[PDB]
Structures are given as structure tokens and as C-alpha cells.
Image (cartoon, rainbow, N blue to C red; front, side):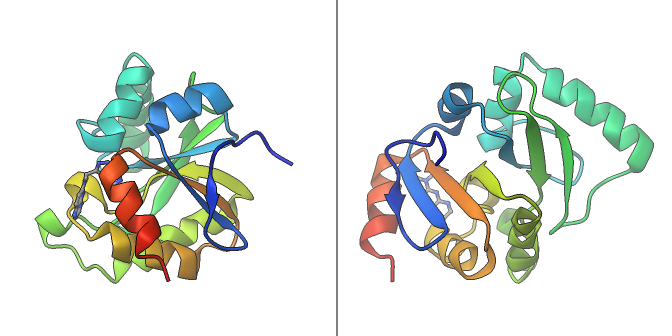
Length: 167
Ligand SMILES: CN(Cc1nnc2c(=O)[nH]ccn12)c1ccc2nccnc2n1
């Protein structure tokens, strides 16, 4: 038993809710919140900008030190950093950005990072300003992640389309 509430169950291990991931994180304090990161950990907009703003920019400060030491992430890769006031840990995961021409096949590699964590609160990777089809992203999530994932979808309209079209 865990503290996630109001989710619809899509499969054995994948759950979904119309929710703002920032508010959901502050209420649940999950062990892991996933950020929709870029390789530079520049949290300017989308989910990343929202999460970083909620940390009063502490996420960005920590991220800049990480990059200065380690260099950029790979598309499809991840790193574990602090969750600040939102979660114990933040798993920064880089899905391909279609608006940068990155290969959509890397979306599966991106979701494989979730399997290193037993339970996660996450957004749909490569959705939103990353330009992928969220229905495709949900399909890859379900077909790749084997650990317990709680997907927060900010847009109610999109949430309804995702549920109603789910096979
Ligand atoms: C309504 N939105 C934005 C949005 N608002 N909240 C969320 C969320 O929570 N996850 C992902 C997206 N998203 C759309 C709609 C069509 C899209 N078609 C292709 C890529 N992105 C798209 N985004």
C-alpha cells in the first residue's frame, strides 16, 4: 500500500491521474519524482521549469554543479539528484525532443531508467514541449516500465483522450 490517491489503473503497474505534478509531489512526497529534463539540466519550461520554480531555483543550482562536474547527460539517459522540497529524489530523465529532431526510438531507452526505481511519480516522457505524441509516449511507458509508475497528466482534455484511447 502507498499514498497515491485518485489514480486510474491502466495495467498491473501503470496508473494515471489528471494532476499537476508539482502539486502532486508536494502532497505525496514520493521517494522519486521524475523530471522531463534536457541534457544540460536547464530547467526553463514545461515540467522542468515548473518543478524547478517550486524548489525556489534550488534544483537549478544543484543541476549546474552536476553539469560542471560531469558534463551533459545523454538523450535517453538520466541522473539521480535531490528531490528538494518535492520528493526524496528527483530522477532527471532525458526523452528525445522532436522539436530538436532527436530519434523517437530513444523514448524506450529513456523509460528504461524508471526500472531502477520501485515506485515513481512521473510525467509522460517527451510529451508537452518535447513534441512527441503523448498517446505514443503512454504506449512506450506501459510496454517498457515494469516498476510501479504513477503518471500525472496536467491537461484534463489530454488526460481524457489518453484514457479513452488506451488499448
Ligand atoms: C495538452 N498538451 C500539453 C500538455 N498539458 N499537460 C500535459 C502533460 O501533463 N503531459 C504531456 C503534455 N501536456 C498537449 C497536447 C497535444 C500534444 N501533442 C504532442 C505533444 N504534446 C502535446 N501536448
